[PDB]
Image (tube, grey):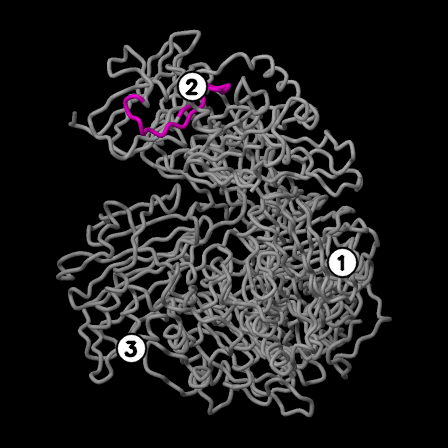
Amino acid sequence: GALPSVGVDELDKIDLSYETTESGDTAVSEDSYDKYASNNTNKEYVCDFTDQLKPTESGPKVKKCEVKVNEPLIKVKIICPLKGSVEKLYDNIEYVPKKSPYVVLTKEETKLKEKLLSKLIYGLLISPTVNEKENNFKEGVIEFTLPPVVHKATVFYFICDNSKTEDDNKKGNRGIVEVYVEPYGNKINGCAFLDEDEEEEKYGNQIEEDEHNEKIKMKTFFTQNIYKKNNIYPCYMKLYSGDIGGILFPKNIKSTTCFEEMIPYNKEIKWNKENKSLGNLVNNSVVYNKEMNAKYFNVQYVHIPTSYKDTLNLFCSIILKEEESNLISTSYLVYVSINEELNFSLFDFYESFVPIKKTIQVAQKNVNNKEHDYTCDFTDKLDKTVPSTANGKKLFICRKHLKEFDTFTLKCNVNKTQYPNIEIFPKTLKDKKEVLKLDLDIQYQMFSKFFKFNTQNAKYLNLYPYYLIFPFNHIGKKELKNNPTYKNHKDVKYFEQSSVLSPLSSADSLGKLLNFLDTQETVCLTEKIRYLNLSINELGSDNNTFSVTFQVPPYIDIKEPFYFMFGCNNNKGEGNIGIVELLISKQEEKIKGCNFHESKLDYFNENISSDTHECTLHAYENDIIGFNCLETTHPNEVEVEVEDAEIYLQPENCFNNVYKGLNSVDITTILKNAQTYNINNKKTPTFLKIPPYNLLEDVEISCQCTIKQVVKKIKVIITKNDTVLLKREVQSESTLDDKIYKCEHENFINPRVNKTFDENVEYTCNIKIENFFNYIQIFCPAKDLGIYKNIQMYYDIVKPTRVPQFKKFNNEELHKLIPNSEMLHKTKEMLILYNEEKVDLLHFYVFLPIYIKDIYEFNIVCDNSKTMWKNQLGGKVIYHITVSKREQKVKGCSFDNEHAHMFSYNKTNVKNCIIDAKPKDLIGFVCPSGTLKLTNCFKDAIVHTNLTNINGILYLKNNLANFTYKHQFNYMEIPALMDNDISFKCICVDLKKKKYNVKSPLGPKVLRALYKKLNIKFDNYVTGTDQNKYLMTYMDLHLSHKRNYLKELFHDLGKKKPADTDANPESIIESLSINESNESGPFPTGDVDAEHLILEGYDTWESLYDEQLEEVIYNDIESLELKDIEQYVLQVNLKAPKLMMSAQIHNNRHVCDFSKNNLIVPESLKKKEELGGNPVNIHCYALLKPLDTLYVKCPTSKDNYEAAKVNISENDNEYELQVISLIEKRFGVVDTGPVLDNSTFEKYFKNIKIKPDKFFEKVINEYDDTEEEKDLESILPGAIVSPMKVLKKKDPFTSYAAFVVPPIVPKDLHFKVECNNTEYKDENQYISGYNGIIHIDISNSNRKINGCDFSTNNSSILTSSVKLVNGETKNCEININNNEVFGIICDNETNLDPEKCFHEIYSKDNKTVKKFREVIPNIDIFSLHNSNKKKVAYAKVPLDYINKLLFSCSCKTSHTNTIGTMKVTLNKDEK
């Protein structure tokens, strides 16, 4: 509802029945109206009617005065002749209104009607101290003031009707003043005191934005809205050269010291505390409504002129009338900064440690030139000044923030006849084009504890203007001296407290400043930014000045905001030092550009190689058109010249000259404020910044580029204001990276430049979850003062229930919507000494339960379209999530009715559950909300007295245990790899004394309390080495249980009341110390790694734990005994089926031999038939190394067993029998029973099969419960493999299969194989055949070794590799000495020569081939020729042979003539 302002009087009373037409009673057509504009002189509009409205014509005439306002802060003055000054001429004049100027005339679709100006125009100021008379007309002046920001184009009429008088049938002239206000300006930089109360965040589109309700528009009038009982935050104003600020004061103010008795905050000179108005501090500053006399709304506007080009800071105290109700502060402070553009300056950073005499300046915004031309003039600020007064030898610091299409120009006076010696800093500015880049890391470190800021937000510290100019530096020192990270810096010495025993001389201060600026790193201009338009002019018009002029491109290729400095040092001549500290912002928007070139930049919206010849671009207001016609793969501006010759751009310059139809016209005619960027030493890419325009027709602009006789056309249709602009949906799809969902949105929440095209766009990412164990990463920050001031995180339920009302979304709503759903955060745990953890607070992770009963579909809204940051509008992201009905449960228990639907097995409210876990099962662990997590299950469990990490025992890599140890619900996948039978207990603690809210994790303090409480050894524990790339930790949403530093800092400031007349705001705010407690983690100095101190990306040090919750936990522990502590225990016991380790005959050589009658033959159970026999998976655990081989013997499958019974008469060779001597006799589970015979072999091994049928030529991944058979060569090439082949012909029973662990293993391997019989069954049915499953677990390595990989020209395993080509001989000599290992890899076409290499080798002659054992009897060769491949081999030379040896092997195509030769040497100059 709308409630009018102060209303009814005898001069403001409105009526709704008065109805008069625009023509009135004169009956004159509007077409024949004699109109002209109001006299506009020096900001003042006057309609002078003293000589116009005179009865001179027989008939009436209409003279209209048009007052058209587009410039803020005007004084509307209307002068029509006095009532009855002369008789018979001014006798019967009438006025509409006679109650003007408070009430005006509005057009109700046909009629002029009386209505108050305050309702359509908010911020009006009419002084009742000049219009107290009943009729303002006896003075003959109608005057009023209009606010500087209006959002409604309103028209009103004033009428001095002189036609009702009659002097001998002569009619007078009726004067009409037409006041028409259009929207100019968006928001005043300032504050408004709202008498209303704060209103809760209206989620979604339920916001009702009415302009009839004055309350709603008032909230949009200033940048700060001060509620008396909620807003503690001091008022702030920022004014630039030519800006307009103000304050809307309340009605309960008693007195104020702002704009008339301001306290100057001066750091350049010593403290002044006197009261000083804007008039004495600033010339030509204009203040409106000073006495606070206006009746409707008491707002004071201050217009700061362009004459002031110095930085000023002022403080104000607004004391409110002491009222009965409680308000946060009866006196509020106001900080007004005038003409400063860069906040958190490094000079303010320096002054808190070393005093600095300086004059900070803004670049001169040129009015006689283009708006985006700015200059800093050190010609008149580089004088020779010896320090004798506090003005001698000052620092002129010129600060200016450049944006899109903005250019800067510096001028120094460098002549030697006025200055004896002057230097330009740095020295490398001229020749190599480098600058002294100012990095913002030090301000990050000093202001890390003053806010909650990460690595990305701290670089935007130069973007936040509200309260970063306070003397916080004087406090930050204490924090900088408190920060254990800043101490280890090389740049500490300049921020150590200066000498006070002897007063520091300014010369030492300036020298220290020069060294502090010198130690910083230099960066090249041409490399940090791409396509810069820069000119270094050492010569002027009289050769007495130096200049540097650089134009900021439209899109900046800086990786991060380019914050640097330069200037001219003249202190070497005992004078001034001129310095410019400048910052270029990174434009975060895609350029609407036609890029036709085949090679294209990565930020052009139209990516056309040769697809389209004509590019249709509809350009809008504030749009950025790009036109590229050249190579983008050239970051230089020297070699791009060769392609400017092959490009023909029409017109010769674009978009300077542009095609309308087919004619070439200067672009400035259609767009007066257009900005064209033409790159130096280039023709294209050219750029057009479409300024604010005013068109009624789609204007077609056109250019064309001819590349290699191909003409491509850009036809940009700059639209009008009334073109159809519909909601544009940008759909992106979920991308599944490492079982976590990611969407490609990086700066679509970050505020970007406002545009009409920037409002009807919505970025929605569709995320479908149809599987288990996948984290849905949602990225939108927590609420903090800056580019994220009013971000909102709410959710709507589409399916199953359709509730279009937007509700709050937090950890609780997500926990309740989906059973046991978890909001988790990605952290990499710190050591116990630190107790902080690197959490990613901008990104959280939705984790869905293993079991899903209802299909859910929702939309998460991260809203930053309400945060307007310097006329830049942020984006909004919609995540359309669909969570499918997934039927998967965990084995275990639930200790209440909360997780019972998660477990197929449940013992509700039963403390200790015992579970037999079998190979590849999937166990879940979860305890009720409020019970204390004792275990890091399933990373760490309890063995019966001790804390033990069950991972290293069970080969538990590649398991959910490793990442699920800090959730509410933890998961674990049983492997087939076991070194023992292990019974552990996953125990959560129920302290019956007190339940908790354990959303935040439990600290090592209380976990040690429970270990010593529950007899759990934290001294005999093998540490679980951090194998996790991450941890999704279960914690509160955005640490809402933890403290908030911004609000608490400003809360202490507001209750410290720095806004009293006698109060000095500095000495009060310096007394503030940031609220900090044990809810935190210290930083130990010494390390195991440096990383526990530094942060990069999106990680920040925060305590996961709640020290209050922790102390309550420790209390309830120490006060109770063991009887009063419930233990929700899952006792998981794992039975490894007959653990066999592979018989390691050599360091390189393991063996899994199974030619036995107790192994696959089902063991003799109890004499009775038990049941359908269950496969006893015979467990061979083979632990090998890079360059290890495993041989595996099993009984021979019936078919090949017979085939070997055939060739029993036939013998092996020296090779195979040799290997035999090396293996069979060289092979717990060993036989004692009957000797193998053909009968029992055929019986028990009738049905023995071997999967994979080719062993190690295909394999079975052991953590793959699908037993997904894979070509290991496809996963790990570089192995030597013999499939399952019969050991001996004479013995039909035993076969073997071998494989080699390659030396470079890019990763851990964990697979398994099976000489599986379960098909043979005991005829008494004890057990089916036993399955011999060998579980192979190989470790990784990446050390390239001597060896020739003729399969590639870059081996990732060997050092040398020159891939062979048929018809080409490729020699690869490698130089080996005693005790060095080598290899060789031939491709499929070239087979080994010899095919017994390495065992046989060409002689030194390369004529004869010899068994290498002969020459060297201790060589360790790794190769098998009982294989399907004869192209890959490896070996090691022994430790005690040094006589000069030479040999070679070759990869020879059996078909064509191809030779890839490895030449192997030994030692060097020897026998």
- Label 1 close to label 2 by CB (< 8 Å): no
Callout 3 amino acid: Gln
- Label 3 close to label 1 by CB (< 8 Å): no
Return the residue at label 3.
Answer: 497
Judge whether 1225 appears above or below 1068 on screen: above
Callout 1 amino acid: Pro
Return the residue at label 2.
Answer: 1215
- Label 3 close to label 2 by CB (< 8 Å): no
Image depth: mark 3 or mark 2 in front: 2
Of label 1 and label 2, which has the lower sequence position?
1
Where does the magenta region start and end?
1414-1433
Secondary structure at badge 2 equals: helix
Q: Looking at the image, which residue sits at the far top?
A: 1456
Q: Position of residue 540 (x, y in %)?
A: 24, 49
Q: Which residue is more in the foreground, 713 or 1401?
A: 1401
Of label 3 and label 2, which has the lower sequence position?
3
348 on left or right of 908: left
Callout 2 amino acid: Tyr
Q: Which residue is more in the foreground, 14 or 702?
A: 702
Image depth: mark 3 or mark 1 in front: 1
Of label 3 and label 1, which has the lower sequence position?
3
Q: Which mark is residue 819?
A: 1
Q: Position of residue 816 (x, y in %)?
A: 76, 62
